[PDB]
Amino acid sequence: MIEVVCNDRLGKKVRVKCNTDDTIGDLKKLIAAQTGTRWNKIVLKKWYTIFKDHVSLGDYEIHDGMNLELYYQ
């Protein structure tokens, strides 16, 4: 299992729950299909890494309990 906190730099705090097996596309939908912040305009990047759907929480060094930057524009 892998927990990922989606810190809304815009002005909010929304924690998420997923796992290594999960992918970027799924994660994007996890938040988008909850708070309604889309999955395209939303800037979901941990520190500064391009989160591509063709992955599984690994290419960007993912751990079970980390924070991610969430910029809304």
Image (cartoon, grey):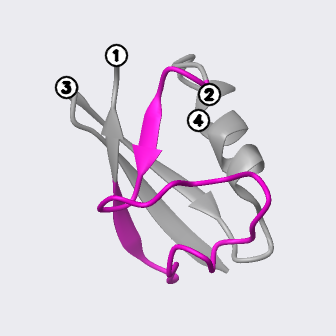
The Cα atoms of the two marked residues, 4 and 2, are separated by 8 Å
Amino acid at circle 1: Gln
Q: Secondary structure at mark 4?
A: helix
Q: In terms of sequence position, does the residue under pointer 2 or pointer 1 come before the other?
A: 2
Q: In terms of sequence position, does the residue under pointer 1 or pointer 4 come before the other?
A: 4
Give the left or right position of residue 67, taking residue 27 as reference: left
Q: Can you identify the residue that label 3 sits on?
A: 11
Q: Are marks 4 and 2 in contact (CB under 8 Å)?
A: yes
Q: Say which of 29 and 59 sits in front.
A: 59
State the image quarter where residue 49 is shown. bottom left
The Cα atoms of the two marked residues, 1 and 4, are separated by 15 Å
Q: Are marks 1 and 4 in contact (CB under 8 Å)?
A: no
Q: Can you identify the residue that label 4 sits on?
A: 31
Disc 1 versus disc 3: nearer the observer: 1
Amino acid at circle 2: Trp
State the image quarter where residue 17 is shown. bottom right
Q: Label 3: few (<14), some or many (≥20) within 10 Å?
A: few
Q: Label 1: few (<14), some or many (≥20) within 10 Å?
A: few
Q: Can you identify the residue that label 2 sits on?
A: 39
Q: Which residue shows up at 66% across the image and 49% down it? A: 27
Expressed as whole percent of the image width and height from the top left, the position of residue 54 reads 80, 59
Q: In terms of sequence position, does the residue under pointer 4 or pointer 2 come before the other?
A: 4
Q: Which residue shows up at 35% across the image and 40% down it? A: 70
Quarter of the image containing the N terminus? bottom right
Of helix, strand and loop, which mostly describes the magenta segment? loop
Q: Secondary structure at mark 2?
A: loop
Q: Can you identify the residue that label 1 sits on?
A: 73
Disc 1 versus disc 4: nearer the observer: 1
**Residue range (magenta):** 39-68
Q: In terms of sequence position, does the residue under pointer 1 or pointer 3 come before the other?
A: 3
